[PDB]
Amino acid sequence: MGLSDGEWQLVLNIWGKVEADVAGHGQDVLIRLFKGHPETLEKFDKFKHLKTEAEMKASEDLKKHGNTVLTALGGILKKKGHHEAELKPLAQSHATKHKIPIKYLEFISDAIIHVLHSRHPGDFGADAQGAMNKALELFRKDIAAKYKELGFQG
Ligand code: HEM
């Protein structure tokens, strides 16, 4: 499931573009996630009134969440697979406190890739697409294993 050094370089180069506007990218990720998979939105009582894309884009609170999520994921990606320390608290909260179904991590991975195509079509070529897919697959695989270790089957 690992990535080569070259693959990690493609991942971190496109992530570098995300880092120019972490909150905005993160907002767009959550908009894609919530619109495409409304069951995910249901996990956020505070966002229940957000129905349209425009309403979601207008929400500074959703933007803050976008920043939270992509800040943590960026920290994980920069470790190039050596992310035990970063993954531990995230698995613990999402498995045992928030109880977020493991499938939703696939949905958010898809959403990240959608946003990268949307914002960076010139710089997100097929090699970067493949490498980013591998990186998100590794993250998902590792956090799914932790979910089970923690006793969360959802
Ligand atoms: C790339 C995947 C994700 C990352 C990096 C991520 C990151 C985080 C971080 C850093 C926090 C705050 C600290 C904590 O409680 O752990 C958090 C809180 C939370 N996350 Fe996630 N998250 C991810 C995916 C999801 C998904 C897919 C959902 C639900 C659909 C979700 C639901 C929550 C909820 C309900 C909270 C508590 C919200 C609050 O009370 O403010 N997360 N997330």
Image (cartoon, rainbow, N blue to C red):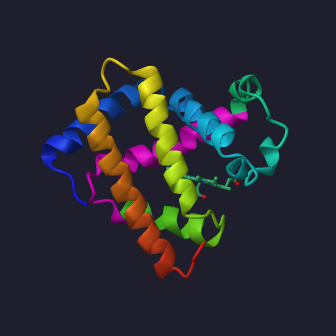
Q: Position of residue 68 (x, y in %)?
A: 56, 43
- Residue visible at 55% across and 36% down? 29
Nearer the observer, 114 or 13: 114
Question: Residue 87: percent from the left, percent from the top?
Answer: 42, 62
From the viewer's perspective, tell me whether residue 89 is left or right of residue 134. right
Q: Residue furthest top?
A: 122
In the displayed structure, does residue 87 sit left or right of residue 30? Answer: left
| Boundaries of the magenta span | 61-84
Magenta stretch holds residue 66: yes
Is 110 in the magenta? no
Q: Left or right? Give the position of 104 relative to 61.
A: left
The picture places residue 67, in percent across and down from the top left corner, at: 55, 37
Check the picture and name the quadrant holding the C terminus.
bottom right
Quarter of the view holding residue 18: top left
Q: Nearer the viewer, residue 57 or 122?
A: 122
Identify whether 37 is placed above or below 116: below
Residue 12: in sight, yes or no?
A: no
Name the magenta segment's main secondary structure: helix
> What residue is rendered at 60% in x and 32% in y?
27
Q: Residue extending furthest right?
A: 49
Asked if residue 19 is positioned above or below residue 131 in the image, the reply reads: above
